[PDB]
Image (tube, rainbow over all chains, first blue to last red; front, side, top):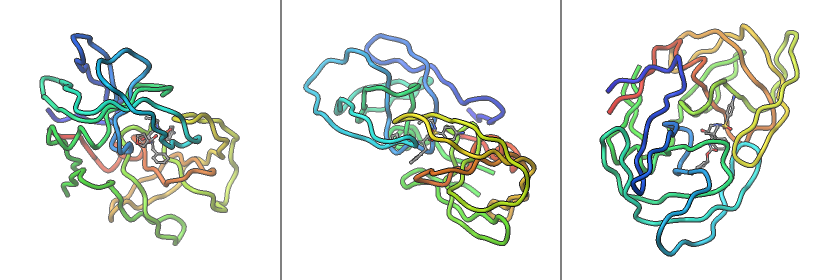
Length: 99
Length: 99
Ligand SMILES: CC(C)CN(C[C@@H](O)[C@H](Cc1ccccc1)NC(=O)O[C@H]1CCOC1)S(=O)(=O)c1ccc(N)cc1
């Protein structure tokens, strides 16, 4: 599907039988989700945003469905103002910018 | 043009005779550029993201050239780690997301 940008590019994602809303963010290198419980061994990590660095929990090889498109990769969970799908998963579903 | 996301979507932008590298960011509602002395009246503002908030100066009606594409709109100037071209300007040059 082709998405215009007059509105926030929000999509419904499915992760762990749960349905959440997330923003397709080409400005984020990684995928960062709001606090939630994911299964598996996670490792502490720190990422930097526009306002500074935060601590997050890193989960590897996580299956996530983005508008019916399957991706399997790294997902960071922590204090983000909103769920964002970064380039690590966008590239998996073949997302590109056009103009 | 078609930009893939294997790497950061960096592009060349022209502002006030100055050419800079900026990120095409569908995740940014508004454009935010690193500190620079732009002429004109401006309004103080606080924007937040990962890590918290930063104070920026809002300028309106600023002419910008994104990869040879003419655009004119609001621009936020402050201590941002990275220059970001947001949806406000992305919609102007007809940029879309595809997959
Ligand atoms: C989705 C959230 C974070 C909100 N914004 C968009 C994001 O794309 C933002 C862009 C950015 C990249 C690198 C350094 C600094 C900023 N990336 C971000 O945090 O990347 C992290 C998450 C994983 O990988 C790296 S924002 O920058 O706060 C923002 C908010 C308001 C305006 N008006 C303009 C920009």
